Amino acid sequence: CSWRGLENHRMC
Amino acid sequence: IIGGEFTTIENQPWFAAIYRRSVTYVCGGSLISPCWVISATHCFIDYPKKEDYIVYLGRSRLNSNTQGEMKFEVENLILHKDYSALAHHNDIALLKIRSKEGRCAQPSRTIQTIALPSMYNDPQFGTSCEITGFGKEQSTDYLYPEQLKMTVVKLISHRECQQPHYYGSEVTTKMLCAADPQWKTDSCQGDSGGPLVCSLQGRMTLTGIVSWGRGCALKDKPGVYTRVSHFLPWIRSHTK
Image (cartoon, rainbow over the protein chains, first blue to last red):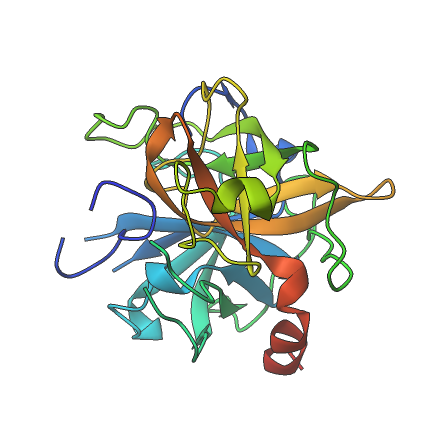
């Protein structure tokens, strides 16, 4: 969740 | 952007700032035509509703209205049907923009488009390109910088990025790795969807789109970008 690829992701 | 330097939109007039309705920054993008902004699918995959998005062009600060900026709504949000995931495949998306006045973007000193590459035509590895974004300045940071930033990273060959001590096979020929020889600078969270711009034959070209990476500015852990010159058919069809 801290890296590129997970921005604006529900799980996070 | 880890390290690098601050800048204003004038230096990257094609950079698009994308937000989601609380109004929070999502990812960057690149203006390729008056009505089209190109970005990364992972930025919207979890909230595909085009109605929750706001795109700005000509904006240099995160939470302030850069004069001369243009606010747009997303008429069409096109995600790549073959998206999969870090290691993120086909991490590319198109946002058709139109203002409330029902118009596309109007070029100016702070709003310009970026040329697309010729198919399978990328700079030679080791070439220095630029990356722009509002991403974190430090991996540990909890906030995104208020001022736009940009930095320089060098293209890495797939054979070298393919190595196990790097990303192994998580990286494919549809991806481009880029990094600092000293790993002192790099893109980071919040820069996704942003442009990797390289000079090709005397022309600033959109060679990549920030996609994914292990941490930020970590040794042997390059930033991975969607290789744009491998998605031209996809782009043209969806933008006809």
